[PDB]
Length: 136
Length: 136
Length: 136
Length: 136
Image (tube, rainbow over all chains, first blue to last red):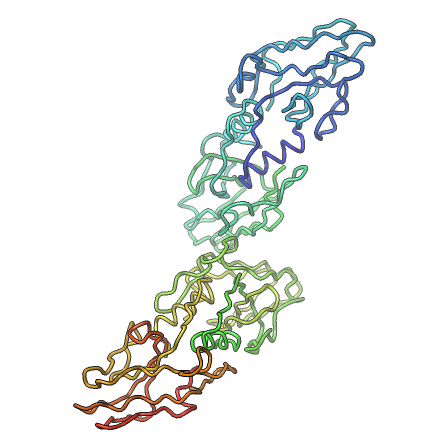
């Protein structure tokens, strides 16, 4: 569940030892379908969800406050992410959650499906409970 | 198949944003039993293999020639790795290989079982053919 | 015992004063019989030994570490040299080694008989020990 | 019969890759005793030979006129070298000649015993015929 950008980066850093790009900020995105594995997703929820601003983790913090320190793996959403409510028109379903380095494009850190499929009505806040969004 | 140390570092770099540690040199190791995955390995073969000077990848080069460029995964050990021949005494059986930062200890990057069981007789070189030690 | 090209360069540099070409990389080879002394050899082992990539001294090193600094003559292979294993077919007899500027052709630096003629079986690596290949 | 300086330089140039110091100008000097092959000779004839100014080869040409180009070895001092006549005092026996890059000191490339032992009277120019002083 690692994109070709991040997989290449980690392999090169571990084996080549070349400079590893450091994600200054982390932006979590909601996608109706799974990303390709490439940069971006196929496809982002647009033209039906007018309020689709990517909720940046650790809103108060600058860097590193989004997730718990690594200890035998695992991560947890320390700060709760409250996505903007669906504006209207048609219902939008969320089945995959993806972490993006940039709010717009900017590579795909992790690509992971949701545990349960959720369909958002005309009005839904779709918060993410703390302690989730773990990675191995 | 990833050690906790390297897993902690990659998770920190990807999500938390800590600067990713980068090896000064790459050392390959041969272990009779699979590494403990934590600090150190179980176990380093000494006093059974009289000459076990760990063979560094990219023997003369500074950095960059260890593995083929990472592109949608896959690696290949560019330079043939040939360990000093078994001096004598008792036979050594190997089933795992681990990548170390330092010639002694220095944390553990990878661990993976050998495809086929291989044993070392009285006198043998035990080279690793180019195209092995691949990383995904 | 030294090839004519090396003889020409040594004498010309010592007396006339023209530029002395510097071998960018040093390659060690094997020949079944005595090389001519001229450019090329009679004869290089190929099509009996399918994998015969000529091993470069200081395999990764740029320059200056392939052989120890001279002290009233004599040098030794700093990095242990290992040729690819004999893929198959029949036995090969190696008696003379040559030092090459280029992997293919490109002058003869040294030619020298081995200590004793060595016969390689179906599968053999035929390594060079550290401290061998001494050249006055 | 190549001294340390030239031997170390040629070995480094051929194997290590260090640049070969080129002699901008070549001197011929004569010594009563055989050279030790080390720095300087053992010993230069001085204070017995007041006029011992080392006749440079290629007196007319700037460089490259002293010796014929190398052709599988062999050389010749194309320019005839005529030493000054001995001023006086005692007879000096000339047995060994050496090549110098500098008029005083400045390394010793070649040491060579002379084929016939020559005793120098009160008067002798002690000239070298063309075709003598070969190199190999």
